[PDB]
Length: 246
Length: 246
Figure (spheres, each protein chain N blue to C red):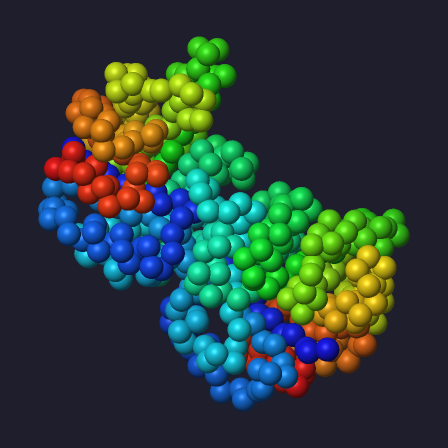
């Protein structure tokens, strides 16, 4: 399968810093038919970022509404995104589950709205420290994946992201070997629910802490197809993370 | 005080519809030094909308983050808005309180962030049908206003909006006089918490159903300083609503 490297800039950026960062990103010569590279800027930065990045880079937004057009102050619908040709959306990032009480049902309905409007979706899930220490990793992941997995109508257009919440801000670290085993089981869930060929087609990204040093050890695992990168994607050195997928 | 007419487009619009609507808006010759007119497009429409609207029209976004810059996927910080010269924010709209569990505590934190970053804030509140039928109108609004009102230093830069939830989708209609009675009570609350000069300074907008037929009767009321308009602001006849404040 085609490797997939994505930059989640989160709530960061200025007009000036994006101008500088996109310029350095543009200096990297890669073939977009050999790997997908997606940048997810803040909503109000999307136009600025899209124009500054060369066409080899894909772009998207960090969240999409579960509702359609109408009386939903502050929301961005999938149909609005389609009209702007916004190619990708992130759904279910743990930060939205944590601070904004986004549920599994919210994730299901957001994916449905996105696919209905021909958007490509990056869907995130993962277990907490308490859940892992109670030996509930498989139980939690299965429930989270089964919340939306049956809706996938194209296995190039939906991309999965494992987020090891147990290793984020806890002092614990997730090893590539531990990541590989989870990814293996995620692909198994997709097999049992969607089919074998579909499971082998779908990309599953690692969504924990990724940097220039650990990136290659992660992507070289058989069932890890790329990353959704946080802090490291705000730096010029992000090009070296992309190089691990080249 | 300076009147204030605002367009809340909510989750509506295409690139083509905005181009057509902004053109009609631009035909209205008004003096921005004597009247405030603000349009609130969808975040991903902001740049498009700002570039098409003549500068006599102020612009803003429909929501702002309670957090600053950092790891908050999907959010737009008050710092990012300032960098883009986004002038206004809407805070505490009933649709965000209803659908996205936004609390009085969220409203306070959003206002603090907005003021710290020198943004101007349109802050909404109001009681439900049940609360009004139990004669709790003043009790509800007093709590809602006191959640944030002590943060206001510049009383030209914070704008209040009364939303009569009891007359929104309930089958009930708020008369202009019934709105006025609440507006006057709100101003008394500001007077007794912030001061007399400050209460006289602050603008209080009506945020219920506003259209071309009722706008004149509303603005005529002594304590109604303008409107935050929903559905009617998506129409070219919105110019007639602005004209009632001229």
